[PDB]
Image (tube, rainbow, N blue to C red):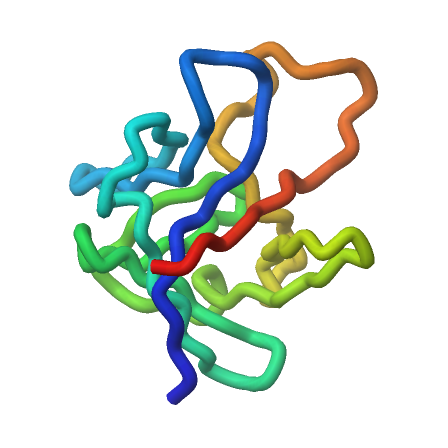
Length: 129
């Protein structure tokens, strides 16, 4: 079982500071600027090309719902928590639900400030954890 511990970091619109993926005990998901353990996710390799992300602090599995929303769960669901590893020539890494092909991104259904023209999924940088 190949597993690694790393912090998920994705750049976004100017704000208080950097934005790091953060999982709450309530099962909510959002970014963090204080960089804490909640933003520490241990990725486990289920099958070649497919991995799972478990929050060590919350011990909750991060799964994406059909609507494409992110949320922590007390149970493992391959059909939603299974993600595919994407590598860009630029050297960035992104995740996409293999089950339905839904893109992985922070919650925000049309509302927060977003530059013109939506590129699509947000880029994530995994820091050693």
